[PDB]
Length: 112
Ligand SMILES: [Ca+2]
Ligand SMILES: [Ca+2]
Image (cartoon, rainbow, N blue to C red; front, side, top):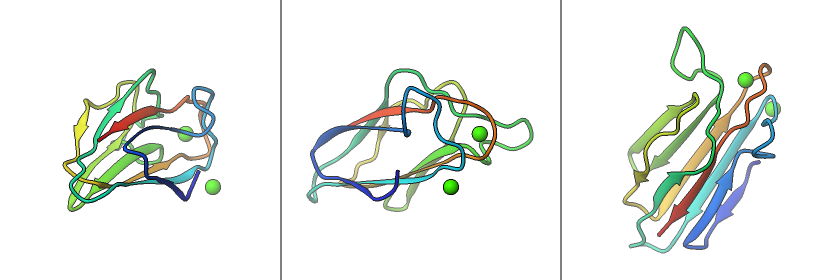
């Protein structure tokens, strides 16, 4: 769940094995890499189910997105964020999980 490079102008990315529980000890990363001038919008779809924590926001299981100097996240819980207009052709996503719990993860679609 590392190394993927997405170069088509639309696509779908999910947590490993979605909608089944994601693996424990996940250290996943993904890149969307389109031609300069393209502008990617990210929209979560379907169920969103990332373990949360009572003491800190999204410490150990989380998704985070970066485009240029902009970072969105970390996100977790049972509700996705609203769609993200990245204003970029170059997007980095990472997804972490720890060794406990049994949550189903995430699905997002991207378009440019
Ligand atoms: Ca691991
Ligand atoms: Ca967990």
